[PDB]
Image: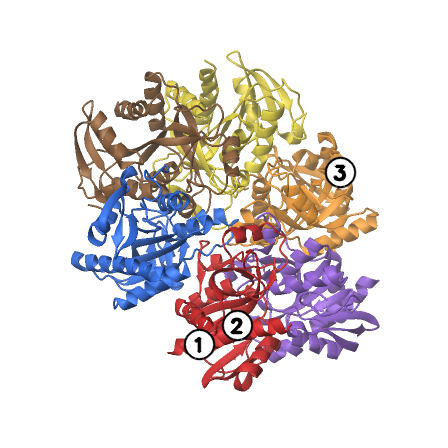
Chain colours: A orange, B yellow, C brown, D purple, E red, F blue
Amino acid sequence: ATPHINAEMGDFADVVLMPGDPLRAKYIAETFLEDAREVNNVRGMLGFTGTYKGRKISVMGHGMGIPSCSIYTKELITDFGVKKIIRVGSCGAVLPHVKLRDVVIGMGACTDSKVNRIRFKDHDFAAIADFDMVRNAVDAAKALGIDARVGNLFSADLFYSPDGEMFDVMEKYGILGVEMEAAGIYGVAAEFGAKALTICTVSDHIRTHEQTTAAERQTTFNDMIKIALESVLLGDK
Amino acid sequence: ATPHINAEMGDFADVVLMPGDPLRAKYIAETFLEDAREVNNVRGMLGFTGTYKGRKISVMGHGMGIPSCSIYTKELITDFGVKKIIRVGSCGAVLPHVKLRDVVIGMGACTDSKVNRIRFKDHDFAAIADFDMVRNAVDAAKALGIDARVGNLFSADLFYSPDGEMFDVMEKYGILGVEMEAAGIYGVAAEFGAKALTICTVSDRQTTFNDMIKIALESVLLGDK
Amino acid sequence: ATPHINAEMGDFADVVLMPGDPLRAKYIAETFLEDAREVNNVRGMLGFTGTYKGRKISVMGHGMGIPSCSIYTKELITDFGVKKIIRVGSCGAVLPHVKLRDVVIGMGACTDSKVNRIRFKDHDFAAIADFDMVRNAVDAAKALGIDARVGNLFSADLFYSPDGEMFDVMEKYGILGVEMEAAGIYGVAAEFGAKALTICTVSDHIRTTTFNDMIKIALESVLLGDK
Amino acid sequence: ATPHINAEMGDFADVVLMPGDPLRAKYIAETFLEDAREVNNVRGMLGFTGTYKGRKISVMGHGMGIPSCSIYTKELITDFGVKKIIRVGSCGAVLPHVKLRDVVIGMGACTDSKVNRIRFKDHDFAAIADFDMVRNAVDAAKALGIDARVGNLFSADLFYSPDGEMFDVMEKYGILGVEMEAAGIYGVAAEFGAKALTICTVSDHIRTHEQTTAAERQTTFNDMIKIALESVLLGDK
Amino acid sequence: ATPHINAEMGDFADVVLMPGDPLRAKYIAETFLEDAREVNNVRGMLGFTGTYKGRKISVMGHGMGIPSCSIYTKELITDFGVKKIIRVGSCGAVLPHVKLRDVVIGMGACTDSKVNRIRFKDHDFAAIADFDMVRNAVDAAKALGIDARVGNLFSADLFYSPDGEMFDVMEKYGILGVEMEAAGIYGVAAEFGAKALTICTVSDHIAAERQTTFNDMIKIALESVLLGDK
Amino acid sequence: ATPHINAEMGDFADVVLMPGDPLRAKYIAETFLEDAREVNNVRGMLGFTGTYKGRKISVMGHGMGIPSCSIYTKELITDFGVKKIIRVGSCGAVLPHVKLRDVVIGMGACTDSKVNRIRFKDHDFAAIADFDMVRNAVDAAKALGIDARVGNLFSADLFYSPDGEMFDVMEKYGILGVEMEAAGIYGVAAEFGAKALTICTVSDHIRTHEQTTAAERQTTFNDMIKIALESVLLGDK
């Protein structure tokens, strides 16, 4: 076990899907995986392992924010033999043509966190996904007939920012979705030698003010999960 | 209701105790409060309201790290009329004379987070607790036969430090304990005009945890007078 | 003697009150201390030692700004056995409801100086006072009928700051008073293992109770700490 | 014309290959393109336009360093209608089994430059390539039977680093190649709304001290040019 | 030889003049130097060695931007025994009384580059010229009857700056000229123990005239070297 | 009068020499000035005005550190018509070839203070002296048979630094002397539109370990003051 996961090597698949919400992890396990078993509940951060079309797969919450997900992703990689992490999250949109419930794939993740500067001697570390994982997601989505845009996310430390003007800058630079984790997970993946990808579903739009309910975020963003799971199968070929 | 809290104004007391672990919040509610009711379970971040010695009190998890607890504390303050937040958590000690099971009260919280720099035009914001709450907690501990240490915490963004350079520096400048939240909560309290305090037990013991919760709850009653 | 203080161990009490102005130190010594003697005059930075209600006490100017007071406080702590430093100064208020002559106690001090970042590997060091000292001062003030405000100071490097809008930021985050030293003194205290406190009187409002009372508060606060 | 390019709209193709070395640009024009004509010589920064397998294509030097290539790529995007830029460069390797003449594709670019912080309110902008261009390069390389790793570059401001320890940090975080431009070009592409990709050839090894000659860098790194040109043809499809 | 300079110790004089444009280096060699010989052409960054009034002089382009000129100046100093470097460039003006064609001598160079912060542990390194060289340049200009201002340049990383407001800040602080190199050259000079100076002519305010003015700058630079030898 | 100077316009000359120690200002007034009179004593920061070779000259302490000297120099400039400020101080050396008693003229001043960053939008402001004042000082020193070094000072915020390694960095980039004021004075002069120069005598060494006599130090001090005073006369011509 590790300080935040009461499990043993073997309990997790070598690929883990990770939403921020452990309740979404539960819904995914119950809906998409066969023979699902709970493999963690420390701090209520539910994780499960099951099979999807014969392929062993795990799904576990990572909590909100870079510091939270950095803990779980590190633990999975060093102690549970996890090779790939697919974050399956929600994000806010700033772009006019990005719509509620759109699926976005974060090839890169910008951030206002200091964690990567701490890692990288105060220079700019480009927090990027694994290329093959990005391509597997894109191809899985095309096979599924689900649209998906690929580009930059922005991983914010403050969901409630005092600096509203930063959204104008994000939009200018083509940021697809604003969430709170991708850059941190990508940093961890680089530090500990694993592969990672963040896929998000647009749960609110910052300019139009539209949003989804907490219940909707918890269970209904299934397009991204299908993409994630099928991308794993492509990855195995 | 907010995106992160499925409740309405009135469901929370004006004072909220917050451990990181929502299961700890459940434990606190079931152990210390009368008539405990679950008032939030969005994302499993359990929140409860009940009474302690007749005083309305809430307890809810804040999750791990500055960004997580920043969300919950802001929403409680701006949407649920919360006036005081007391974080009740664990910390790792750095000093030789700061023993295991010691109670530490964070009058200040250092951090390697950028959030307060974002707030404060890239200058040094001293992230501090509300003094009356600190005094209340010190007095409540004394009444219970405990000498709490009062001083600086360090709120880390990285539980798993890439290099661990900061540990010796924290020791050098007299930091009492390392955790992952206080500096963020204090920033929120300052930003939105509320009062906050972080209390921790040195974990690097069900008695001392209970002791800390008793300190927090009794400190609130002191503040009410 | 140290590079900036021509005195020897024993010349200073283990508690030193420090105004920015050395002539204010002279005034405090003549007004409050019995059998006061001058113990330093290097650079005109007048220091004195005497007694207050029988308690040995020193008072000495620290000059203006973090770099200046950092020198004097370090030398006092490392070479003269000083355990407690109490800065007694004036500050500007940015909050509407803070009044002229309000007393402010800096439990913390924000700053735009780089000194604590240099100490703290470019992270945020929370520059704080010693809790017991803060409490002693609150209690001493209350005994005199004064409700001191307890919270953050901001220690500016520039008295003539080019960034007026920062004062709005200070107001938004609840800064009680603006001066030029607290954060530096608190960094020195942490660095060298001592205790410090800054008490200020509000002398003006930035942008569009007496001094003797403040000194009494600081001195009486020491007596409480002794008990 | 623009301040650094004496040419007119239409003189450049909508895709431009750019080495930092204008003499490599000249070699590429003479060697890979038919009917190539010089379209720029301002400051000796040679630019050419010709066809590759019937497709109009340009190649032009961008000079050494972020500030130099930022000027040229900006002027090309805003004033000559250029839609895609492919940097075709050289780089130093820090990883043990990245060897001389290996081709590396920068899906991202780290940097110690301040330019993106200036653009992005002092936060972390993830300087990334256009995904489709990355995939086109990967596919072209596969078709050509040429190996090419995809990952992070590091765009340095100081070829001669005072801080040698930074190479250890690059190595730790899996940096494939150290050059001096990708992150700047990616920042310009984002700022002015175009698409970019950096492909490099390993010209020296920072650890073993193996290195190629100035002549070899000028005129023998042809694998990366084949990939770049074939990838454009894929993108057109 | 170095990866960016195909030449050997001795091919260069111990003083090198450097415009950004290698073609202007070629012009200088051809115009003011005798017996000029091309000594570098890697990346087309032309370098020449000749004599001016009997004194061995080199001139070579440095390309655009701090990273570019930093490579050339470093290599000239460490591998080619170069002692003094004089940048002879163009700049943009932000001050009212600074006119097109004015000659500015950069005793200092401000910058928005991170290179000196990298050198100097994230503190403020004042990127300054060598005093004697500045004085030689001022004295030569006087001898030639050319007026010159001595002050701060600003070395910008982005010719196309997203931050329009910074030019107001430069003006407020008396920046004489905005170019893209001096601060980097000065950092190199300090790092490797050589001497440097940047002289610029104002080419913009943010034909035959530009010629005369360019020549004037070159004459100041060359004549200042002679003064420095004395 | 101003908040830190209880004097009236005309009480100061248009040139003010400024040592850190107000007692040194008194010494200078008594030793070099005719008909000296005290014109300030607020905070014990003694200032005097008199004549040197018939020329009106002032001398006033500035206290220790950037924040202290920034207050005094600003007030002299905006409210007392002061055009030139000459700091005359002591400094520590880091270079072995820089000897105790050397005279150093700070044409530039590096610093670890944030004050110039605050002024200059977080970029690098080169804190410099006025060129003519530097030249006047070099010439005055020559005429007195003294060879002054001209280059960079480093203005430190911390006389007792926790960062011992910074001295190696200073040495590496050729810093001549370490003091605590020059960069702040130069920042003020630039902000409020006056001219400044800092001259220092080397009084200690961080790397070497010579030791002088008080007699030698007073001679050298006097030498520096003569240089400052004579440099003013040169500038008047």
Residue bearing the label numbered 2: E217
Residue bearing the label numbered 3: A221
> Would you say the residues marked 3 and 2 are in contact, meaning their CB atoms lie under 8 Å apart?
no
Q: Nearer the viewer, residue E102 or A27?
A: E102
Label 2 lies in what chain?
A: E
Vertical placement of C149 versus D210: above or below?
Answer: above
Q: For numbered disc 1, what is the local secondary structure?
A: helix
> Would you say the residues marked 3 and 1 are in contact, meaning their CB atoms lie under 8 Å apart?
no
Same subunit: marks 3 and 1:
no
Residue A153 location in percent, x, y?
67, 47
Where does the C terminus of chain C fall, quadrant-wise? Answer: top left
Residue C170 location in percent, x, y?
49, 34
Label 3 lies in what chain?
A: A
Residue bearing the label numbered 1: E225
Q: Which residue is at 23% across, 47% downward?
A: F36
- Residue furthest to the front: F54
Q: Amino acid at mark 1?
A: Val
Question: Mark 2 or 1, which is nearer the eye?
Answer: 2
Same subunit: marks 2 and 1:
yes
> Would you say the residues marked 2 and 1 are in contact, meaning their CB atoms lie under 8 Å apart?
no
